[PDB]
């Protein structure tokens, strides 16, 4: 009856709701990975901790419980800090478990001795180095609860080697119960009535449904709220799917005109950050009334004054708004100058998009490639879209129908999360298909992770590379003594990386090769790579 | 006419609700204090930034909007981080405005150049170095709003000298409006009913009223709650006053008894920290069920599992409880085996208290001295108690009837907040009398600030020193080569410091002098000091 | 036999050369202060850890081994970060020992649980929380060694409660030997001959003697080099005493003219920071050639380029400059246009200084008061001068004849170091007298420490308060509502604080009261206070 620290941590994580663990083993975190599998936690051995830390953050967004990134002492943990910042920026729960040198070797210049707690502090809600084996379950339970309660964030546990490998009696350790699900605070009664009056007194109302509404699991109530009020709504890049992107109330093609003309905006789990242009002119009405629904009280009132503050959980507050529509029913009129003005902009944009999508010139364009892509993604798949032009075009091109089904660079604009987040999507959804659509540069960050996807049999992932030979484009030839900083090797056969694990690679340059190569890639028994070449001068609209 | 960065900061502070500023002037924050008085902010020049930063955190607890501590670059700002940590520990809104060297001198070894941002960060919710003059009102509103929203805390603004001395067109500076009061969060209706179920099913219930409820300013709602349900309640040291200490529902004389045998406990703005012994045995039921009411979601479930999590503002949640109680009337029975057990200990403990306050022996004891102080403090006064035994015995002997009328060491257990919090209490309540009962050791931390109190005419403050010649006691004689590390000068006449500003000092050794000296000091036109000698053996 | 962690760290501190400890006791650092006295370390209980941490940094400058500031967990340690920063700014060795809650209570909201390592690190060369009891001497030896080797600085030791109270058999504890003194590296012969060739070519040379040369204890070698070369030298505020302030080679009364007209400058343990105007115009020649002698290689070349870099110990490199002169003797001539120019400004500034001292009017001025103070201070006493004008006017008027005999605000310009530094001076030098000349504003930062000085029988300290009723002056009548932010109580009786411990206070307001009150305060058997009133509108020599 002797239990080790790695055993205690592994069982504690499984008890507190951890199911997926990513990272790379080594001194001294080897036992933690072995016991994680022996306790019911799937461990995925990545090729670089940077990509593994991004996968851990994506699990916190998809499942509601934090994903664990395991890194060795010193540099292994430091690589994982990149993911901590991403979870810090996107408000996602995630745990970074970093090994450390033997505590009795501190100050001696031990192997991989580093100020790991201080390196994780700027992006962590919680840092801790446990003091004893018997109190390890206290730190794990506190680490999980801190990551999901309130505004979700990243936490870090510093595990010295002697605690990982030390042993003690099992009857003496105490395992706390699985901490309850994150409490859902509600808005005050008087504020819900004030939020309705502002919406009922709006000439040009607008609803913004963002990442916070998707993470809050509030898809049912938002669809009930919008369909009952018939309000025009705008989805964030990762709010797509909370409300179906083919819904009539969506004004996404007229995004710029809606934000510029709106006088009362309802924020549903979204922030007025760089993505929303800080809510300031010339993109917004300088006197726009703002109703903000957010779980963080400090976020309320950022950049733009907030007239009605709905501090609390997006799912708990939206039920109050739905409860307001029962003792006081109200619908927004279906024919106003605001509706007809917007609906003209959508039909104009959609005509321009289709006119650009139907162009078949070679070298191909984004819209031409995204036509064959869009018509082959099933309505229940998971889109992973990383890149610059590729990601932005696909945002408006590829629709989503279920919540939390699109993953991109997020609020931090991080390159390198792509293949990492795609593996996390296949670990959470092993029966659904994941489309990891990448640019040539973004794929180069975590490109070696294609072998990881195949080693765990994640054939539900199809890697699609939109290549234009550089960051925003590159030439057809390169002078080795005069390479542009953004240029890459022209016509780089990235798809030949599929031969590492015996998979299929496709090199597409003409619209005829597009659909057949894509069709056979999805049917493959191993993760296939489709490398599509486009024009370097191809741009947006 | 043009406006300077110092004048921009002062007006923006006043607009966002700042009314009190403490600190010491100097390079380069001198113009800030000048426009502070000019824009209507009461500035108080302290003797040390350490005591000033504690007065700032006290104003945040008393008013609901953060007091400001103004410190010079380098050493001045670093001294103010103490109060930042105190507000960080007590969840109080507080602002430290530390000057900096001119930005065009960074890296040159400028005057008082220091990593001030990194020094404040471990205790700050928000550190910011404003980038330009036009955006100064943006950072000021963001600092105040971040200090009072959510769980209150301390923030820090790094103001370089050139930002302070620079000027620009006044009409080109945009001042955001006064940010609204801290938004109230409410608990789900199912959580209210589950808390009522646990309280109704409780064999031995207990309500712990903490200072989080006092800061929430829910005294009117907590009294409607407890008076309706007749639940026995225990108030934290700074939770006193939310309910009058003479209320029959109080079980404070038997604190160690109720915490030991309470099957269901209701935490009303109270934290299960070291004060509550972590909610663990031997002082707690190993299976105690907790109904936790706190605004910080991360705090819920700490140390002890929380069955009913009432996350949100204490005033809004208590209002839900009262609304539920008047639609579903329930009262804890007045005759219970639980009521008859605590009441016996309350009567038994109260008997030993009376037999200790009747002690007339010289040197005196804590209980004899506090008996006369208790008889002379009105019901509307404010008590500031600091020390160890002096403060703990004063917690159980001083009665508080209005909320937020007692200021002690706080959740940090800080020695040095005494005179700072007393000065803050006198500036917020110039109409009430402020009692500052200090230990001789605690008085050494900030006793120089009696001049600050006298300089601003704060004759409503009475400094009472309870002197046992050291930290928990001191010997009668001292040899300089054999001074105990906890001993001070025997019979140190601290009251002589009242003669610095021409005040009255009093030296009491026998109970015959207690009442006359205390009554004479309250009537003094200048802040008087009463130095009371007590026995080093009394416990 | 079993030994506790408190006794392990107390013995290890004494073994590593720690002699003085300042702080305030309380949970959980009580056994440390008790066991320190049992092991030979002298503990001084202050009234505030802030003043104690300033006293601990002063011990490092006076002795070369770090003084220790002892603080309780949480707020006790945070108060002691001020001294860490002051030692960090002045490059002095200093150790802050802060308590911490029991390790088995982390994350529980324990009593005074705080992120103390992070609070100290911005000013720390070394932060460490010892992992076990048997390795406590390892962390003590490394902390001392780090604080004194290379560029000296402040270190921090984080001691949890159960590390202090735990015990184990004394045999298993390895006590490392007393770490050797700081090594004294030196410059190449090429750099030595180049620096000597630079001085030999200077039309208008100037030598700057900073407290880095004082800390290095190179007073004999500096006096041997300067008296051989006859080079005009300027002494920084705490660089005074390395050379006798009454030296014909001193051009301090003409500091502005010397720094401007100089074309070659030798930096002896002094930085080109705010105190030296960054070596920039209009106070310096734009084409000034600089020879910099500094222990820190990273400091070489700051603001102004360094033609000749002499990286190493000031005492070791000055020895090389003397060996080079013993083989190639060279003297700067004493009748140059550079000399006669500086002396013309010196004689005229000295006349204006002598005139302001002759003023007998009431209220008195800084010069009349210092005229009497200067004449009652022995040539081997220690000067603690803190304030604004009080500190700056005193530096020109208070001559120091021995190195490391003046303590002021330092490179950080700190208010609150005064009384703490005076107590540390008296503890190091109980034979010499300590004069603590303070401004009325500066005195209030740590005024309660007068009782600490009396409690330990420090009769060799005399507290002198130059009172102008505010920060740089103040009115003579105060309305309690309309209070200037820089003014204090008019005619405050700070001398009454001496009566706390039975001492004697003196309230001086006339010139005929200075000498009788000052002469009797020095001879008191308890530390006395002399509160001297001056004019609020009193300035310095323009
Ligand atoms: N369960 C929840 N209920 C309400 N708000 C939440 C919840 N979880 C996160 N949020 C808030 O949602 C916000 C995230 O918005 P953001 O991701 O920037 O919008 P976008 O979708 O445009 O990226 C955060 O400020 C966070 O506080
Ligand atoms: N407006 C508020 N409503 C509810 N809880 C609050 C509010 N403001 C602060 N709190 C909480 O009250 C708690 C105060 O507990 P503590 O400082 O330990 O006081 P005490 O122990 O004296 O009750 C903090 O944890 C804080 O999160
Ligand atoms: N033993 C030593 N030998 C040489 N230089 C030293 C030694 N100790 C410290 N120093 C240097 O002295 C410098 C201190 O300069 P500073 O305090 O600015 O002098 P001052 O204030 O007297 O002008 C530091 O840069 C430090 O590197
Ligand atoms: C970690 C990180 N590194 C770098 C960047 C900057 N960045 C943004 S997009 C991009 C390259 C885009 O690659 P790709 O998809 O090939 O470009 P596109 O063809 O879509 O323009 C880079 C380097 C970033 N946002 N994050
Ligand atoms: C900043 C700080 N320094 C030191 C302490 C340790 N401490 C706790 S209570 C106390 C003073 C106790 O003495 P006193 O105030 O005279 O009261 P007594 O208990 O003797 O009546 C001290 C120094 C602390 N809590 N905070
Ligand atoms: C910690 C700290 N707080 C504040 C200052 C600003 N400051 C510089 S000098 C000084 C005091 C000036 O008054 P005083 O000591 O009476 O000197 P005087 O003008 O009489 O010479 C102050 C507060 C500082 N340098 N350090
Ligand atoms: Mg590209
Ligand atoms: Mg005492
Ligand atoms: Mg003055």
Image (cartoon, coloured by chain):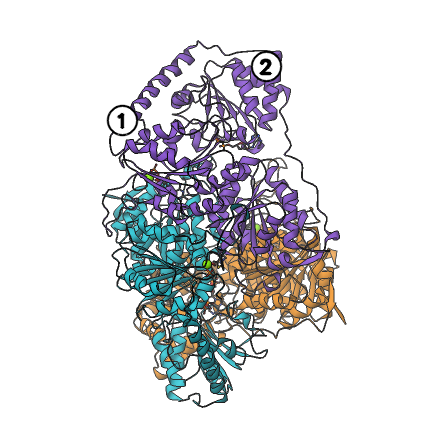
Chain colours: A orange, B cyan, C purple
Q: CA distance from mark 2 to mark 1?
A: 47 Å
C391 with respect to C233 (left or right): left
Numbered badge on residue A413: none
Relative image position of residue C266 (x, y in whole percent)? 51, 22
**What SS does tag 1 mark?**
loop
Relative image position of residue C166 (x, y in whole percent)? 66, 59
Q: Residue at x 31, y 74 (%)?
A: A197
Which residue was labeled with disc 1?
C359
State the image quarter where residue A273 is shown.
bottom left
Mark 1 belongs to chain? C
**Where's the N terminus of chain C, which quadrant?**
bottom right
Outermost residue toward the right?
Answer: A1
Q: Does the beta carbon of the residue at mark 1 sit less than 8 Å from ligand 6?
A: no
Mark 2 belongs to chain? C
User: Which of these two is toward me, B352 or A372?
Assistant: B352
User: Which of these two is toward me, A136 or C460?
Assistant: C460
Which residue was labeled with disc 2?
C325
Q: Residue at x 45, y 27 (%)?
A: C279
Q: Earlier in the sequence, mark 2 or mark 1?
A: 2
Q: Residue at x 43, y 10 (%)?
A: C336
User: Which of these two is toward me, C150 or A241?
Assistant: C150
Q: Does the beta carbon of the residue at mark 2 sit less than 8 Å from ligand 3?
A: no
Relative image position of residue C11 (x, y in whole percent)? 65, 47
**What SS does tag 2 mark?**
helix
């Amino acid at each position: 009856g002797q239990i080790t620290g790695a055993q205690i941590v592994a069982r504690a994580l499984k008890q507190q709701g951890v199911e997926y663990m990513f990272g790379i083993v080594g001194i001294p975190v080897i036992p933690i990975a072995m016991f994680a599998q022996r306790e019911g936690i799937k461990f995925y051995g990545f090729r670089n901790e940077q990509s593994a830390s991004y996968a851990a953050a994506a699990v916190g967004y998809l499942t509601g419980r934090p994903g664990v990134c395991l890194g060795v002492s010193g540099p292994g943990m430091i690589h994982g800090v990149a993911g901590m910042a991403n979870a810090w920026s996107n408000c996602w729960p995630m745990i970074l478990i970093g090994g450390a040198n033997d505590s009795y070797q501190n100050g001696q210049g031990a192997f991989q001795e580093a100020p790991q707690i201080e390196a994780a502090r700027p992006f962590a809600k919680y840092c801790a180095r446990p003091d004893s084996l018997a109190r390890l379950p206290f730190y794990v339970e506190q680490a999980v609860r801190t990551s999901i309660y309130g505004r979700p964030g990243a936490v870090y546990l510093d595990l010295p080697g002697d605690i990982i490998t030390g042993a003690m009696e099992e009857e003496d350790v105490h395992f706390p119960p699985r901490c309850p699900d994150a409490p859902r605070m509600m808005a005050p009664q008087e504020s819900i009535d004030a939020a309705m009056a502002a919406l009922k007194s709006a000439e040009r109302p607008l609803v913004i449904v963002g990442k916070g509404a998707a993470y809050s699991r509030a898809e049912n109530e938002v669809r009930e709220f919008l369909e009952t009020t018939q309000l025009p709504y705008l989805a964030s890049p990762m709010g797509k799917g909370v409300m179906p992107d083919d819904h009539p109330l969506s004004i996404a093609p007229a995004r710029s005109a809606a934000l510029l003309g709106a006088d009362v905006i309802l924020l549903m789990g979204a922030r007025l950050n760089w993505m929303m242009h800080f809510g300031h002119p010339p993109r917004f009405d300088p006197k726009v009334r703002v109703i903000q629904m957010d779980i963080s009280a400090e976020e309320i009132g950022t950049n733009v004054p907030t007239e009605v503050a709905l501090v609390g959980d997006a799912k708990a507050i939206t039920t109050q708004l739905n409860a307001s529509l029962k003792q006081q029913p109200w619908q927004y009129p279906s024919e106003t100058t605001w509706w007809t003005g917007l609906r003209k902009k959508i039909d104009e944009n959609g005509a321009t998009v289709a006119e650009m999508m139907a162009d078949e010139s070679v070298p191909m364009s984004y819209y031409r490639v995204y036509r064959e892509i869009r018509d082959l993604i099933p309505n229940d798949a998971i889109i992973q879209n990383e890149g610059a032009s590729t990601m932005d075009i696909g945002r408006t091109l590829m629709p989503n129908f279920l919540p939390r089904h699109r993953l991109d660079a997020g609020s931090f604009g991080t390159m390198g999360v792509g293949l990492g987040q795609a593996i996390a999507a296949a670990a959470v959804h092993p029966d659904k298909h994941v489309f990891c659509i990448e640019g040539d540069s973004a794929f180069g960050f975590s490109g070696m992770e294609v072998e990881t996807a195949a080693r765990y049999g994640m054939k539900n992932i199809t890697f699609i590379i939109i290549n234009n030979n550089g960051i925003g484009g590159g030439p057809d030839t390169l002078d080795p003594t005069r390479v542009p900083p953004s240029a890459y090797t022209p016509n780089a056969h990235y798809e030949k990386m599929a031969e590492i694990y015996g998979g299929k690679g496709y090199f597409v340059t003409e619209p005829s090769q597009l659909r057949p190569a894509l069709e056979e890639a999805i049917k493959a028994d191993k993760p296939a790579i489709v490398n599509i070449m486009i024009s370097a001068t191809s741009q947006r609209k």
